[PDB]
Image: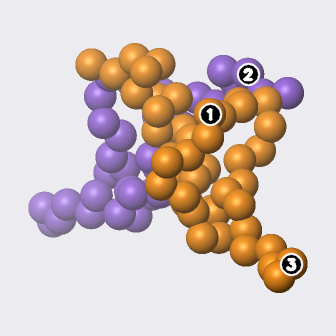
Chain colours: A orange, B purple
């Protein structure tokens, strides 16, 4: 049976698939903020 | 800010998008069972 340790596990992962160039070892999350993986921002 | 009345609202909806021919006025849900919309099954 599912719990909140499976729903909130899967709630972020489909939110993670809108990351342009996503990550693998992600930082800790924040449910009250949107999630966006670090985009390529060139300065050099 | 989000609550469980937005996360569990959106947890079923992306689960709803795997329905081959989904519905509009859906039946009440069951979180411990998978969700599958009524497929076309011909008998006539």
Residue A23 in which image quadrant: bottom right
Residue drawn at (27%, 19%) of the image: A1
- Marks 3 and 1 in Cβ contact (< 8 Å): no
The residue identified by callout 2 is B3
Q: Secondary structure at mark 1?
A: loop
Q: Are marks 1 and 2 on the same chain?
A: no
The residue identified by callout 3 is A43
Give the label, 2 or 3, closer to the camera: 3
Q: CA distance from mark 1 to mark 2?
A: 19 Å
Residue A39 in which image quadrant: bottom right
Q: CA distance from mark 2 to mark 3?
A: 38 Å
Number of numbered tags placed on the structure image: 3
Q: Disc 2 sits on a residue from what chain?
A: B
As drawn, the label of residue A28 is 1
**Image x and y of residue B26, in percent:** 51, 41
Q: Residues within 10 Å of mark 3 (few under 14, many from 20)?
A: few
Q: Residues within 10 Å of mark 2 (few under 14, many from 20)?
A: few
Residue A40 in which image quadrant: bottom right
Q: Disc 1 sits on a residue from what chain?
A: A
Residue A29 higher or lower than A24, as above or below: above
Residue B3 higher or lower than B34, as above or below: above
Residue drawn at (17%, 65%) of the image: B42
Foreground of the two, B29 or A25: A25
Q: Disc 3 sits on a residue from what chain?
A: A
Q: CA distance from mark 3 to mark 1?
A: 26 Å
Give the label, 1 or 2, closer to the camera: 1
């Amino acid at each position: 049976p599912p719990t909140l340790d499976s729903i909130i596990t899967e709630y972020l992962r489909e939110q993670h698939a809108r990351c342009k160039n996503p990550v693998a070892t992600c930082p800790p999350f924040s449910l009250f903020t949107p999630h966006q993986c670090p985009e390529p921002k060139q300065r050099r």
